[PDB]
Image (cartoon, rainbow, N blue to C red):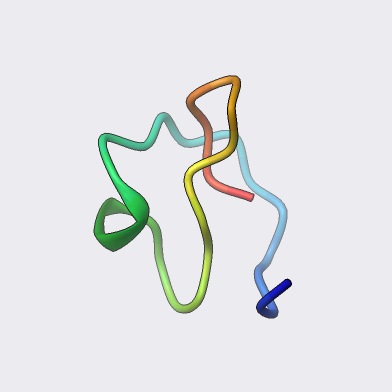
Length: 30
């Protein structure tokens, strides 16, 4: 439940996501 700007970027892991963005189940940063 970390703060994260909504963007459509495919994540290969949470660390792949900017800031405190997490890798959503659909495989995007959220």
